[PDB]
Length: 80
Length: 81
Image (cartoon, rainbow over all chains, first blue to last red; front, side, top):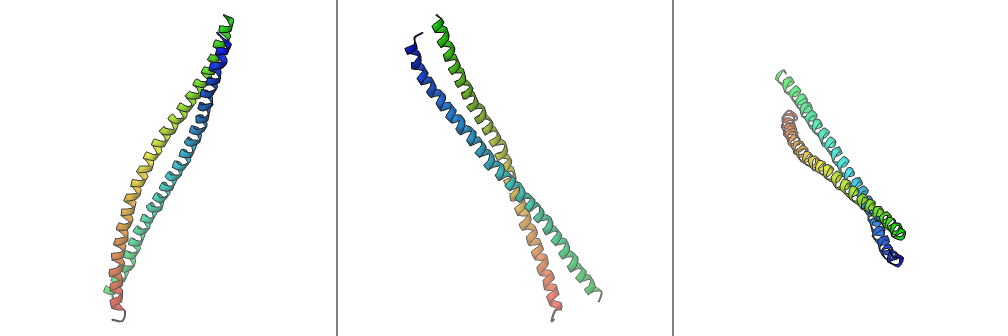
Protein backbone atom coordinates (compact mmCIF):
# COMPACT_ATOMS: atom_id res chain seq x y z
CA UNK A 1 0.00 0.00 0.00
CA UNK A 2 0.78 3.69 -0.39
CA UNK A 3 3.53 5.53 1.50
CA UNK A 4 1.73 8.86 1.78
CA UNK A 5 -0.85 6.54 3.24
CA UNK A 6 1.75 5.18 5.66
CA UNK A 7 3.30 8.33 7.16
CA UNK A 8 -0.38 9.09 7.77
CA UNK A 9 -1.18 6.26 10.18
CA UNK A 10 2.43 6.40 11.38
CA UNK A 11 2.23 9.88 12.90
CA UNK A 12 -1.02 8.81 14.54
CA UNK A 13 0.45 5.51 15.78
CA UNK A 14 3.35 7.34 17.44
CA UNK A 15 0.74 9.28 19.42
CA UNK A 16 -1.07 6.21 20.85
CA UNK A 17 2.33 4.88 21.85
CA UNK A 18 3.49 8.15 23.37
CA UNK A 19 0.42 8.14 25.66
CA UNK A 20 0.64 4.52 26.81
CA UNK A 21 4.30 5.10 27.69
CA UNK A 22 3.29 8.12 29.77
CA UNK A 23 0.59 6.24 31.68
CA UNK A 24 3.07 3.39 32.10
CA UNK A 25 5.18 6.01 33.92
CA UNK A 26 2.20 7.11 36.02
CA UNK A 27 0.89 3.67 37.04
CA UNK A 28 4.29 2.47 38.16
CA UNK A 29 4.80 5.61 40.24
CA UNK A 30 1.29 5.35 41.70
CA UNK A 31 1.69 1.70 42.62
CA UNK A 32 4.92 2.35 44.51
CA UNK A 33 3.56 5.43 46.26
CA UNK A 34 0.41 3.55 47.28
CA UNK A 35 2.60 0.62 48.30
CA UNK A 36 4.88 2.72 50.52
CA UNK A 37 2.12 4.72 52.21
CA UNK A 38 0.14 1.60 53.05
CA UNK A 39 2.92 -0.70 54.30
CA UNK A 40 3.89 2.21 56.55
CA UNK A 41 0.42 2.58 58.04
CA UNK A 42 0.38 -1.16 58.76
CA UNK A 43 3.71 -1.39 60.57
CA UNK A 44 2.52 1.68 62.48
CA UNK A 45 -0.62 -0.13 63.63
CA UNK A 46 1.22 -3.36 64.40
CA UNK A 47 3.51 -1.38 66.74
CA UNK A 48 0.70 0.33 68.67
CA UNK A 49 -0.65 -3.15 69.15
CA UNK A 50 2.56 -4.41 70.73
CA UNK A 51 2.64 -1.06 72.50
CA UNK A 52 -0.88 -1.70 73.79
CA UNK A 53 -0.36 -5.45 74.18
CA UNK A 54 2.41 -4.70 76.60
CA UNK A 55 0.75 -1.74 78.29
CA UNK A 56 -1.81 -4.40 79.21
CA UNK A 57 0.66 -6.87 80.77
CA UNK A 58 1.92 -3.95 82.85
CA UNK A 59 -1.49 -2.98 84.19
CA UNK A 60 -1.79 -6.67 85.05
CA UNK A 61 1.58 -6.56 86.80
CA UNK A 62 0.53 -3.41 88.64
CA UNK A 63 -2.66 -5.17 89.76
CA UNK A 64 -0.61 -8.06 91.15
CA UNK A 65 1.91 -5.78 92.87
CA UNK A 66 -0.83 -3.60 94.36
CA UNK A 67 -2.50 -6.75 95.67
CA UNK A 68 0.88 -8.02 96.91
CA UNK A 69 1.68 -4.89 98.90
CA UNK A 70 -1.79 -4.13 100.28
CA UNK A 71 -2.45 -7.74 101.25
CA UNK A 72 0.96 -7.84 102.93
CA UNK A 73 -0.15 -4.79 104.87
CA UNK A 74 -3.50 -6.36 105.79
CA UNK A 75 -1.78 -9.51 107.04
CA UNK A 76 0.69 -7.67 109.27
CA UNK A 77 -2.21 -5.64 110.66
CA UNK A 78 -4.09 -8.81 111.63
CA UNK A 79 -0.89 -10.09 113.23
CA UNK A 80 -0.02 -7.10 115.43
CA UNK B 1 3.08 -6.46 -3.47
CA UNK B 2 6.41 -6.30 -1.64
CA UNK B 3 5.58 -2.73 -0.64
CA UNK B 4 2.42 -4.01 0.98
CA UNK B 5 4.49 -6.73 2.64
CA UNK B 6 6.96 -4.19 4.00
CA UNK B 7 4.45 -1.69 5.39
CA UNK B 8 2.29 -4.44 6.88
CA UNK B 9 5.24 -5.68 8.94
CA UNK B 10 6.02 -2.10 9.97
CA UNK B 11 2.46 -1.57 11.20
CA UNK B 12 2.56 -4.96 12.94
CA UNK B 13 5.74 -3.83 14.69
CA UNK B 14 4.17 -0.60 15.94
CA UNK B 15 0.95 -2.45 16.79
CA UNK B 16 2.63 -5.10 18.93
CA UNK B 17 4.83 -2.57 20.71
CA UNK B 18 1.63 -0.77 21.69
CA UNK B 19 -0.06 -3.99 22.80
CA UNK B 20 2.84 -4.84 25.11
CA UNK B 21 2.67 -1.31 26.49
CA UNK B 22 -1.08 -1.66 27.03
CA UNK B 23 -0.50 -5.04 28.62
CA UNK B 24 2.12 -3.55 30.99
CA UNK B 25 -0.33 -0.84 32.12
CA UNK B 26 -2.92 -3.51 32.88
CA UNK B 27 -0.66 -5.96 34.80
CA UNK B 28 0.76 -3.14 36.91
CA UNK B 29 -2.60 -1.66 37.88
CA UNK B 30 -3.89 -5.21 38.31
CA UNK B 31 -1.20 -6.04 40.87
CA UNK B 32 -1.40 -2.58 42.45
CA UNK B 33 -5.11 -2.93 43.24
CA UNK B 34 -4.72 -6.50 44.50
CA UNK B 35 -1.94 -5.73 46.97
CA UNK B 36 -3.79 -2.58 48.04
CA UNK B 37 -6.82 -4.63 49.10
CA UNK B 38 -5.02 -7.44 50.91
CA UNK B 39 -3.21 -5.01 53.22
CA UNK B 40 -5.86 -2.36 53.77
CA UNK B 41 -8.07 -5.26 54.83
CA UNK B 42 -5.24 -6.35 57.14
CA UNK B 43 -5.02 -2.73 58.24
CA UNK B 44 -8.69 -2.83 59.22
CA UNK B 45 -8.05 -5.93 61.26
CA UNK B 46 -5.39 -4.13 63.29
CA UNK B 47 -7.52 -1.02 63.82
CA UNK B 48 -10.16 -3.29 65.35
CA UNK B 49 -7.54 -5.16 67.37
CA UNK B 50 -6.48 -1.78 68.75
CA UNK B 51 -10.05 -0.85 69.76
CA UNK B 52 -10.31 -3.94 71.97
CA UNK B 53 -6.87 -3.44 73.53
CA UNK B 54 -7.79 0.15 74.34
CA UNK B 55 -10.92 -1.07 76.13
CA UNK B 56 -8.81 -3.57 78.07
CA UNK B 57 -6.33 -0.88 79.13
CA UNK B 58 -9.05 1.47 80.36
CA UNK B 59 -10.63 -1.54 82.07
CA UNK B 60 -7.53 -2.54 84.03
CA UNK B 61 -6.67 1.11 84.70
CA UNK B 62 -9.97 1.50 86.56
CA UNK B 63 -9.44 -1.76 88.46
CA UNK B 64 -6.02 -0.60 89.64
CA UNK B 65 -7.38 2.86 90.49
CA UNK B 66 -10.11 1.40 92.70
CA UNK B 67 -7.59 -0.94 94.31
CA UNK B 68 -5.09 1.85 94.98
CA UNK B 69 -7.75 4.12 96.49
CA UNK B 70 -9.14 1.66 99.06
CA UNK B 71 -5.57 0.69 100.01
CA UNK B 72 -4.69 4.35 100.37
CA UNK B 73 -7.83 4.74 102.46
CA UNK B 74 -6.73 1.87 104.69
CA UNK B 75 -3.22 3.29 105.09
CA UNK B 76 -4.49 6.79 105.90
CA UNK B 77 -6.63 5.46 108.76
CA UNK B 78 -3.47 4.17 110.43
CA UNK B 79 -1.60 7.40 109.76
CA UNK B 80 -2.33 10.10 112.35
CA UNK B 81 -5.51 8.29 113.41
